[PDB]
Image (cartoon, rainbow, N blue to C red; front, side, top):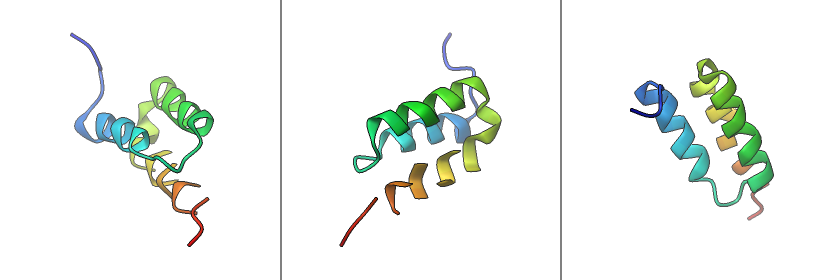
Length: 58
């Protein structure tokens, strides 16, 4: 009765939530954007995943 999102879309949500290095503010931005338009699932995911990989020093 909740989450009118496809598997990929909901996966994007969770995967962006699974970004511990990503600023929670940016996380909220991507998540909210996913809520606004989940059509950008694969690619808000591609590039939250990729600020998460790219604020990552080594």
